[PDB]
Image 1: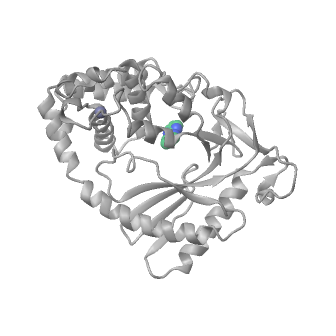
Image 2 (image 1 turned 60 degrees about the horizontal axis):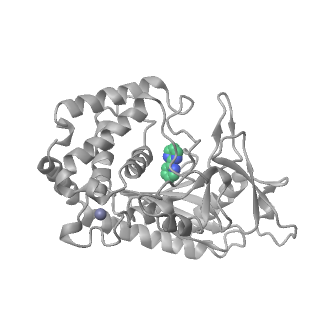
Image 3 (image 1 turned 90 degrees about the horizontal axis):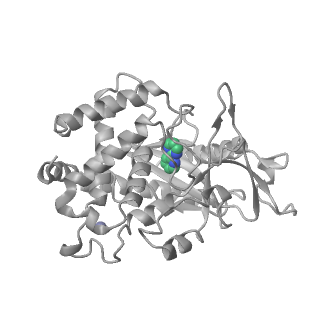
Length: 361
Ligand SMILES: c1ccc(-c2ncccn2)nc1
Ligand SMILES: [Zn+2]
């Protein structure tokens, strides 16, 4: 494509940081008061803020009125029960025998109910947003699954609040062959990263005709954040002029491509199933394929970008996009996304690439 064109796109994209940060401030305030009022309840005592997502990864673009926050909650001594070889969805039981468990009320049998937890969560949040008349914050009717609550700050800002269980235990076995960063960020880093906790968000699993509503999906957004904000083989990568790479620029460009394409065909349902996480996952795989900083030279911004696109396209055609942490978990399976959508997105991206990306202007 050429470096300078994409770079112009990146300038135009860079112009929104001030506004996005300004809204992020208000979000921060509201969420702060919320968490302050949430820790009162015995069930959500050890609840806290989890600073992950596009904003904290410094890759959020062109959506200042939309934010996603995650609330983490420490669940000690838990036992995970894998659902139907899905490798990613789990039942949360408790290995702890005493009734000292603060989540006993949400225990539907030996298994911890996600429905009860989410219900109490939404209830407490509703009461606490009703309690405050200082700021103009209102909840929203239930729609999505993983985004538990949806808030509206003033009558402009929109915040998606997600709840996540935190486990300081060692990661599930399905993550064993994942996080292939050995040749990129070193085995040492992979080793110390796996010593960090893992998270679980309430997400129902698709069987085909019905959905299991009492399951939890693995989450490693903190690991994604760490990797993105420390992305080079060199520790001083992007800390001086001679060591400037174009990884994050490529990620931004991909995210922007998908956003613009989703916007152009928004009156249909073809691209509704695709999200930024797909793009990010593909990006991480490309990073694994090209572990050297010299393969991400600034002047090569064009080629690199194409690389990403190319790989993404491949994932579309072969209907295979492995989760970066859970290899046997396929984000692009026919169960999750139908062939027609993938072929449509392939068609569009290929057109764009064949005509110097007119969607970038
Ligand atoms: C954080 C954000 C999104 C996701 C996800 N999005 C779509 C399909 C599967 N996972 N996972 C983690
Ligand atoms: Zn770098």
